[PDB]
Amino acid sequence: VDPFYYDYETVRNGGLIFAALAFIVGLIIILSKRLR
Amino acid sequence: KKFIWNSEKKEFLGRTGGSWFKILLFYVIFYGCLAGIFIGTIQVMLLTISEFKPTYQDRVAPPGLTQIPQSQKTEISFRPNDPQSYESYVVSIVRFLEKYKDLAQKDDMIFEDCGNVPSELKERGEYNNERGERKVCRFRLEWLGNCSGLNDETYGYKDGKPCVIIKLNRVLGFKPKPPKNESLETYPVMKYNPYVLPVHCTGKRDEDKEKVGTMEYFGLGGYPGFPLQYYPYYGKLLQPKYLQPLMAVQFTNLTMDTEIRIECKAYGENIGYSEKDRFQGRFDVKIEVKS
Amino acid sequence: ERDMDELKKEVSMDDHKLSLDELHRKYGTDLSRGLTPARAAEILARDGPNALTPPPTTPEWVKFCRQLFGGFSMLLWIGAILCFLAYGIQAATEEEPQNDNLYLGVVLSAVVIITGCFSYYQEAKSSKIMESFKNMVPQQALVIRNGEKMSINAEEVVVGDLVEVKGGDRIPADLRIISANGCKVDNSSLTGESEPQTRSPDFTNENPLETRNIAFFSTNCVEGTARGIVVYTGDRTVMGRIATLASGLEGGQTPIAAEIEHFIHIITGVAVFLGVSFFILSLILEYTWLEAVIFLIGIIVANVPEGLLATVTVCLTLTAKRMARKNCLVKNLEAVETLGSTSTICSDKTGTLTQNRMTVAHMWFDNQIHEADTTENQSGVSFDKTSATWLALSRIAGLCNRAVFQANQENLPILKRAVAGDASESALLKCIELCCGSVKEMRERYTKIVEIPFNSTNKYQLSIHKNPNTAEPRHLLVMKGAPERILDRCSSILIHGKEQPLDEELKDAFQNAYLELGGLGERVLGFCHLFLPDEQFPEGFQFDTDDVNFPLDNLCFVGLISMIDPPRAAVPDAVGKCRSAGIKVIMVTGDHPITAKAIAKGVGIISEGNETVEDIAARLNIPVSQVNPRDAKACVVHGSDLKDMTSEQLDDILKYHTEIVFARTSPQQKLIIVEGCQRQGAIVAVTGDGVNDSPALKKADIGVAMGIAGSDVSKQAADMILLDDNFASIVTGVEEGRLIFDNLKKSIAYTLTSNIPEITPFLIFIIANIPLPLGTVTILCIDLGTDMVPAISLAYEQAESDIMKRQPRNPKTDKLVNERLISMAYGQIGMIQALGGFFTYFVILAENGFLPIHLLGLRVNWDDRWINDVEDSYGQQWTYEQRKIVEFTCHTAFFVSIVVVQWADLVICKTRRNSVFQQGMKNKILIFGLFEETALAAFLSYCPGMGVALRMYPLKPTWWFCAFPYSLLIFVYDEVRKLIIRRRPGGWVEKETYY
Ligand SMILES: *[C@@H]1O[C@H](CO)[C@@H](O[C@@H]2O[C@H](CO)[C@@H](O[C@@H]3O[C@H](CO[C@H]4O[C@H](CO[C@H]5O[C@H](CO)[C@@H](O)[C@H](O)[C@@H]5O)[C@@H](O)[C@H](O)[C@@H]4O)[C@@H](O)[C@H](O[C@H]4O[C@H](CO)[C@@H](O)[C@H](O)[C@@H]4O)[C@@H]3O)[C@H](O)[C@H]2NC(C)=O)[C@H](O)[C@H]1NC(C)=O
Ligand SMILES: *[C@@H]1O[C@H](CO)[C@@H](O[C@@H]2O[C@H](CO)[C@@H](O[C@@H]3O[C@H](CO[C@H]4O[C@H](CO)[C@@H](O)[C@H](O)[C@@H]4O)[C@@H](O)[C@H](O[C@H]4O[C@H](CO)[C@@H](O)[C@H](O)[C@@H]4O)[C@@H]3O)[C@H](O)[C@H]2NC(C)=O)[C@H](O)[C@H]1NC(C)=O
Ligand SMILES: CCCCCCCCCCCCCCCCCC(=O)OC[C@H](COP(=O)([O-])OCC[N+](C)(C)C)OC(=O)CCCCCCCCCCCCCCCCC
Ligand SMILES: CCCCCCCCCCCCCCCCCC(=O)OC[C@H](COP(=O)([O-])OCC[N+](C)(C)C)OC(=O)CCCCCCCCCCCCCCCCC
Ligand SMILES: CCCCCCCCCCCCCCCCCC(=O)OC[C@H](COP(=O)([O-])OCC[N+](C)(C)C)OC(=O)CCCCCCCCCCCCCCCCC
Ligand SMILES: CC(C)CCC[C@@H](C)[C@H]1CC[C@H]2[C@@H]3CC=C4C[C@@H](O)CC[C@]4(C)[C@H]3CC[C@]12C
Ligand SMILES: CC(C)CCC[C@@H](C)[C@H]1CC[C@H]2[C@@H]3CC=C4C[C@@H](O)CC[C@]4(C)[C@H]3CC[C@]12C
Ligand SMILES: CC(C)CCC[C@@H](C)[C@H]1CC[C@H]2[C@@H]3CC=C4C[C@@H](O)CC[C@]4(C)[C@H]3CC[C@]12C
Ligand SMILES: [Mn+2]
Ligand code: NA
Ligand code: NA
Ligand code: NA
Ligand code: NA
């Protein structure tokens, strides 16, 4: 009922999930034992 | 001196004439195409927003309580005896109120006569060109009690009784909602018109509240607030000469030669506050009549 | 020098006067068997390793302080200190303050911490790799223990140990000579004179330095062999203390430092200029008195590549590691770059181009060519083993020989056993031992009276033996050597047993046989003997080897023996790469010109179609002296001709010939060739293994000492050590050296792009009077996020596809940072990266209510804190913080957009000539950097509290995709530019954009 309200929590958690995924994948690549 | 100019191959600052011409032409065509791509992307973005409706507004919600005269550091200090120490506030008040002059609201194709008492939201329709330009609810300058620039041009500063006209931040498609009297147990005693957004000024500490004096609220119908019959706002494209509701507060009987900080607050469901934004729904003005 | 002869000759006290018995009871060593490994370890643990104590090492925790509180770290600490100081002022002024300055100071301090921690990681890695090479192949010492002779690390030599040194070995420690056979030492580093002083066990002088029975540490043994006993080890030796307290090296201006220090100075100057100019600009634009200095600090930190030192360190250390893994050990780090600039390689034939594994192949006697060496079927050879001439040939091939099989090897095959002697002598041994009989038995029967070994002056081997036959004259002389010299020293030739005068027809057949055997690429040796008359030489005759008591002329030629020596496997492809890389290969061998030419044509030094003057003359049957020398692109220069050659003739031969082969060239003449090549303005790498090569190895730009057969003198005089003695390894090292230039250039070209988008927002802020699109905190975010890890990741990039298909570079033309690199980083890529950020800024402001046109001039009121009536394009009124939220969200989106375009910049910086599709994304560290920078941006934009601490607010989804077009634009632009360069070499596009 609040048109002047954007669900900032949804985008925030979406971006944080992405940040965690990218961080984990980066660690997997740099610490990879079989990616070379 | 060799780097500055060598004439053998006609090199100036490092390269020959043909070199300068070639790099200048490359940079001209490159920067031209770059600025063209920038402008093109800007136009493609412009084709997404509309002329009378912004794609995002949660950054202006809730609106802010603004005060006239606007003051640097929000301090209204002057010497009532000296007519010069308060000329700045008078100039600002006159410049803002001139848009509300009795002569400014002449034509009826723009200005429409709205009720002398606060009424319900006068919904003009939708935000398109189908209904063309829109009507403007007139606001009589006389609705301000003793500060109208009609009988006393000074507005009170001449005899140590200033006036700070309060105003609400214009927000497109905003419908103020006064608090229901059922919930009325927190805010102080005020007149209750279900079509009036209330505003109440007080001190801030146990010292300013005492040294303040006697508040005098002036507004449409004698209600300390804004009448709901002036909202919603339809933007600057549909209502070019829209006049927003005003309200005045006169601080009669203020402690001379003493600075007192007062906070005015607009209550309502749609009106929030913030500890970081000292103007979101409320505001602060410290006044000192040092005569 | 105030450090030598009178001060050193007095610090001396030795035991050269002791007898072998007194020496034995003093040191307690079995003078014929050495000490037991038990006592060796005991003395090693008691006295310490045979090494000199090194200077102190900076603590493992001091680099942290030197980096965290260094040059730019001091600037960031000053900024954070000022922020904390202003927070104290605000905590003392009006009650109910704000903590903006506390968070700004915490931010700056965290920036210093992260920057110093990353730089420390990189520098600690540099230390970890620098140590890995000083002990990769340590210097060895040949000691004798428990009777067995074993080679051990020089640091494990203890006092009393008996060491055995030979020609080319370094003296492991001060020794007392017990036994020696013609041993000569080079006391140049000790007394100054490089004249070889002989060393004998006999006591000759009271002064320890003037005596002849003491070998000194750090000196080298030139010729001979000697056994001694360690009297001083480590720091106790004569030269030990002197050399370590006076051997400080220089501060050599390597081209890497020559370019890096300069470019860093200019970039630091322009950055500090921008910082102060923006400082005064901000102060004029009513900026707060503290945020102006913070903006100056941020500008200085961002516009300066504060990781170029780490990038250079990682590049040089990584490529040094890569070279060491490919059998190229660099002694110093200058060679790491000189290798990439190599243009001429003077290599040897035997030892570097070939495996030096010789096997007898053909013989020439009785005017007939005889193949031999049956395939282990007990058949022997392809001729009768009873031929008289072959008997005389194998007789002098086993008698005049000097190599012997080692202990316990007469119970296994002959082509799989071990030997002791030259490669040629080993092949001559394995031949007659596999097809005639026992060489030890034959050499025992013909007792050797006197012998002349292989000397550089004689240039031939010889031996006189007692003859036990019946139709035998008492003494039989046998000699071998260069076939030409052996033929000139003979009057008769042995034909089927009967000798006959050496006529012209036989000499012509000999020359034709030499051409036949040498055309196959085989080393040929001459053999001859003489039956010394009894009237002139009775039984008890004593042949003088110093006055030529016996005749050396009028000999009798027996035959020619030729051995095969296959070239290395990767040599042909290596010379092919060199030809494809503009590197001139020159063969410098002491072999015969026929064999040298054959081997060169086989491995590709002399390519098909090219002919020497001799080949032209032989093709059109004209005198060689008549042919035009310019008609031959290749040539075979003889050593005797180089001796009678002038500097101008040498320069002529080198300048007007593309394929040069120096045959019969002595190791001393190598320096002449090196000087001639350097005189032509070329970087020369020269291969050396002997002690006579030292001048040529030190004079050359890159001396390559053989890692296996190379003596310690060559290894100590060389700039690089070839671990597998393979020529192809030199070319591989050259490619690795060429890789550092590309990687460093790419990393530099990537680090400079972000400066334009980091400074343009403030410039437009002043010129256009619009709300600031990029703040200080976000500038620091851009620097820490996209400029640290992605810039280092370029150092790990692999070689391109045309790394060896291009031409070498010279220092005075190919600079690290040139005008084209600045134009590309600042004028083309940087501008697009900045435009992307400006675009997303306009998008955010327009979507929130402020159209781009409305933003002109609005900044005056936008930055005002008391004007809360700011009207947008839609006519709405905003407060101060309400609009500041949008401005800071624009800052965050600007940072995100910069990351997005930095993706494309990092990808296009992977290749500067080829396309990214041929190279591929094989770099794992680069992909890691991309993922981590994107994750860091997402975290700094969506983590709770970032809005109230770093003023960074969440980004709406449709805001991440606003910079994609500019990123793709950068990608396609660089791809088409590189495609145009590839399909139009030397064109305008390359001559103006190829950085
Ligand atoms: C701000 O707005 C307010 C309204 O919101 C104005 O209100 C005024 O407040 C005062 C204080 O309460 C009232 O009381 C007294 O006013 C006296 C003067 O008025 C007397 O005469 C009037 C009749 O004549 C007046 O009106 C006609 C038009 O009708 C004019 O033509 C004529 O010239 C006169 O102006 C009567 O109607 C009125 O009741 C009075 O009899 C003051 O003299 C009086 O002072 C006494 O009280 C003081 C304490 O307050 C004390 O210090 C004095 O010693 C003395 O004992 C008192 O102020 C006003 O009636 C009321 N209206 C008006 C029109 O003034 C207020 O005026 C305005 N601010 C200013 C600065 O004007
Ligand atoms: C409305 O506003 C006023 C403030 O102005 C408040 O009441 C008083 O108003 C006067 C007038 O401005 C103030 O100033 C002067 O105070 C002097 C002090 O003397 C008396 O007061 C002290 C306490 O301060 C006593 O201890 C002492 O014994 C004295 O009795 C007076 O001498 C002044 O008198 C002069 O002015 C009056 C009218 O202005 C004339 O008629 C006289 O002839 C004389 O010239 C004057 O009173 C005073 O300080 C104010 N008192 C305060 C602030 O406490 C009202 O309180 C305020 N209304 C409300 C509802 O709060
Ligand atoms: C009004 C405000 C204007 C602000 C302008 C701000 C410009 C900021 C740029 C800063 C970075 C400068 C970095 C220099 C790095 C040099 C590194 C180095 O040693 O390189 C060797 C290289 C040289 O390499 P080389 O020596 O190997 O090659 C030499 C080649 N020949 C012989 C042909 C010359 O250095 C350079 O090329 C120096 C280039 C300097 C360029 C200076 C450009 C100033 C232009 C300003 C434009 C202002 C436009 C205003 C428009 C307003 C419109 C309204
Ligand atoms: C406005 C619209 C813009 C659209 C832009 C994109 C257009 C094209 C569509 C996709 C392109 C982008 C994805 C490319 C993937 C390429 C993969 C690859 O290995 O290509 C191999 C190929 C090489 O293939 P190859 O090496 O197997 O084959 C070579 C064969 N020979 C040897 C014969 C030549 O190289 C590339 O295409 C490089 C692409 C690099 C793209 C880098 C993008 C940034 C990378 C990471 C950023 C962060 C991502 C975070 C993701 C988080 C997800 C939750
Ligand atoms: C109606 C049509 C709609 C099309 C929509 C888009 C479809 C996807 C478009 C591109 C994605 C696939 C790109 C493949 C590129 C070549 C890969 C390759 O391995 O070739 C090897 C060849 C190299 O082979 P090689 O011979 O050099 O390597 C030899 C390997 N050995 C030694 C083993 C034999 O690649 C090249 O030479 C590359 C030239 C590239 C020039 C690129 C110019 C344009 C810039 C970017 C391209 C577009 C990016 C996407 C844009 C999207 C826009 C929406
Ligand atoms: C290989 C290259 C070209 C592709 C780069 C990957 C792109 C598609 C990734 C990189 C960062 C990502 C964003 C990270 C965070 C958010 C917040 C979330 O609530 C919506 C999606 C959104 C906006 C993501 C969309 C996908 C995204 C833009
Ligand atoms: C950031 C803003 C204020 C300045 C940007 C101005 C642009 C036009 C500047 C930035 C870097 C500059 C280039 C830097 C170096 C060279 C080499 C010189 O021999 C020819 C001009 C040329 C190619 C410059 C042309 C102008 C240039 C492209
Ligand atoms: C280089 C150019 C020509 C590529 C052509 C495609 C252009 C027109 C496309 C590519 C990516 C697109 C942008 C992607 C995301 C956004 C966010 C949205 O809320 C406004 C439009 C905007 C900004 C788009 C505008 C159109 C756009 C810029
Ligand atoms: Mn040699
Ligand atoms: Na930087
Ligand atoms: Na050298
Ligand atoms: Na970059
Ligand atoms: Na930068």
Image (cartoon, rainbow, N blue to C red):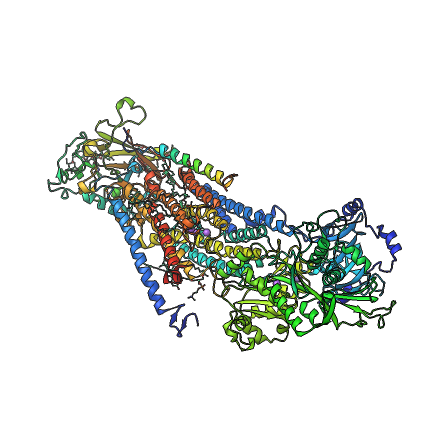
Location of residue C929 with respect to C600 vertically, above or below: above
The outermost residue toward the top is B182
Picture quarter with the N terminus of chain B? bottom left
Q: Nearer the viewer, residue C767 or C594?
A: C594
Query: Which residue is drawn at the image coordinates 11% and 40% (left, top)?
Result: B109
Picture quarter with the C terminus of chain B? top left
Q: Position of residue B111 (x, y in %)?
A: 13, 39
Side of C876 where C147 appears, left or right: right
Q: Position of residue C886 (x, y in %)?
A: 33, 42
Q: Is residue B172 visible?
A: yes
Q: Position of residue C667 (x, y in %)?
A: 65, 66
> In the figure, residue B201 lies in which quadrant?
top left
Location of residue C323 with respect to B132 vertically, above or below: below
Location of residue C489 with respect to C417 vertically, above or below: below
Q: Position of residue C721 (x, y in %)?
A: 62, 56
- Tally the numbered discs: 0
Q: Nearer the viewer, residue B71 or C394?
A: C394
Q: Quadrant of ligand 1?
A: top left
Q: Nearer the viewer, residue C220 or C73?
A: C220
Location of residue C524 with respect to C59 vertically, above or below: below
Q: Is residue C96 visible?
A: no
Query: Which residue is drawn at the image coordinates 68% and 67% (left, top)?
Result: C482
Side of B277 where C608 appears, left or right: right
Q: Nearer the viewer, residue C955 or C181?
A: C181
Query: Which residue is drawn at the image coordinates 34% and 64% (left, top)?
Result: B22
The outermost residue toward the left is B108
Side of C856 where C337 appears, left or right: right
> In the figure, residue B211 lies in which quadrant?
top left
